[PDB]
Amino acid sequence: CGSCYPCSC
Ligand SMILES: [Cu+2]
């Protein structure tokens, strides 16, 4: 990241 921080989405 984003919305799923930390990722992979
Ligand atoms: Cu992320």
Image: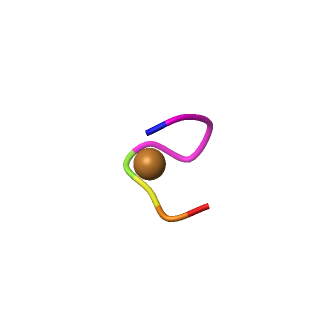
User: Where does the magenta region start and end?
Assistant: 2-5
Please report the residue visible at 44 percent of the width from the left and 42 percent of the height from the top. 5
Magenta region, main secondary structure: loop
Please report the residue visible at 62 percent of the width from the left and 37 percent of the height from the top. 3
Q: Quadrant of residue 9?
A: bottom right
Task: Examine the rendered structure and indicate whether residue 9 appears above or below residue 2.
Answer: below
The answer to if 3 sits in the magenta stretch is: yes
In percent of width and height, residue 1 lies at 43, 39
The chosen color scheme is rainbow
Task: Examine the rendered structure and indicate whether residue 9 appears above or below residue 4.
Answer: below
> Is residue 1 toward the left or the right of residue 3 in the image?
left
Number of callouts in the render? 0
In percent of width and height, residue 2 lies at 54, 34
> Is residue 3 toward the left or the right of residue 7 in the image?
right
Task: Examine the rendered structure and indicate whether residue 9 appears above or below residue 6.
Answer: below
Please report the residue visible at 44 percent of the width from the left and 56 percent of the height from the top. 7
Q: Residue furthest left?
A: 6
Q: Residue furthest bottom?
A: 8
